[PDB]
């Protein structure tokens, strides 16, 4: 069970673009599975992905 | 902006989905830079609804 309501709440997130669905609606739908791809990139190319 | 949610988008003040108008933003870091820490600027936190 994921607390997707509160993960969005941390104000550290400076570039929070949810192309998939709206952020607040992360709470209701049930995910088949999930990919969690983590890395660190340049400050300029943050929006190239 | 109409189409965003957050502490700055709904918890303090909301823009309607049919809003028409002009937002204006400019760099007031000159006057707003207060040696007293300008802590007189508040906002409600995480209101239970929207």
Image: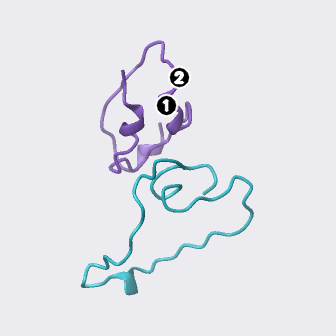
Chain colours: A purple, B cyan
Nearer to me, A31 or B46: B46
Give the residue displayed 31% in from the left and 79% down from the top: B38
Q: Give residue A40's position: percent from left, percent from top.
A: 30, 38
Give the residue displayed 72% in from the left and 67% down from the top: B21
Q: Give residue A34's position: percent from left, percent from top.
A: 42, 18
Give the residue displayed 75% in from the left and 63% down from the top: B20
Q: Do the residues at discs 2 and 1 belong to one chain? A: yes
At mark 1, the secondary structure is helix
Nearer to me, A12 or A28: A28
Subunit ID for the residue under disc 2: A
Q: Give residue B14's position: percent from left, percent from top.
A: 59, 59
- Is residue A19 toward the left or the right of residue B47 in the image? right
Q: Give residue B35's position: percent from left, percent from top.
A: 24, 85
Residue A26 badge: 1
At mark 2, the secondary structure is loop
Residue A7 lies in quadrant: top left
Q: Quadrant of the N terminus of chain A?
A: top left
Residue A29 badge: 2
């Amino acid at each position: 069970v994921a607390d997707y309501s509160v993960l969005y709440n941390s104000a550290s997130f400076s570039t929070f673009k949810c192309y998939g669905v709206s952020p607040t609606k992360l709470n209701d739908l049930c995910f088949t599975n999930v990919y969690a791809d983590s890395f660190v990139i340049r400050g300029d190319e943050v929006r190239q992905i | 902006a109409p189409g965003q949610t957050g502490k700055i988008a709904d918890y303090n003040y909301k823009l309607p989905d049919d809003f028409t108008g002009c937002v204006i933003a400019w760099n007031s870091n000159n006057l707003d830079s207060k040696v007293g820490g300008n802590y007189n600027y508040l906002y409600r936190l995480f209101r239970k609804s929207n």
